[PDB]
Image 1: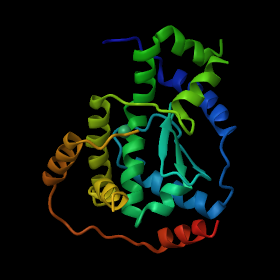
Image 2: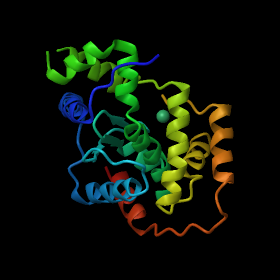
Image 3: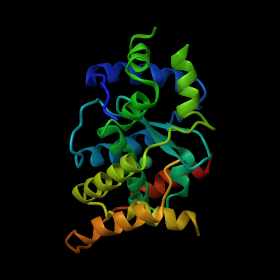
Length: 223
Ligand SMILES: [Zn+2]
């Protein structure tokens, strides 16, 4: 169960390599305004996180599927489809806060190390074509990085805290899920755990300025 973990510095390098490989199959958004907006919400959430140990980069990708995913080394990809599906900035932030916390807790590199072993992960770091196999399998359009129940719970727990500290209503993620119904599996357990975490916080009115969100969403539906 225990394993040798690569260093923060080594993971920065792993992320660099994954990023360039993953991006070969993506169509980027090259819209400074959309870029600026996602950067802002991401930066705001990071101010609420427990540890910011990477220079986080938020990349918006042209893809109608509803997804966001962190890769090793603090790089978070956000699909245009997610931005278009979100009803408000709070929903968007809820999804982003969960993914940021997978990065904060180093879940990607932990899961890869438990699955493949330290030697393989270290070899990715050093670049010993294996890196290309893994990019596709973990992070491509049919690719499932899949996190243990424990890591999902951690990302949920931290995401509620992150949202709260950043001044967003922590119900954002579950609200997004409800709207969607009207691989990060939203199980009975996760709903119960998230509701309990939210229940422990002081009741308060969450203030939002949806100006920028509505502008950006508007621009994306034009594409
Ligand atoms: Zn997750």
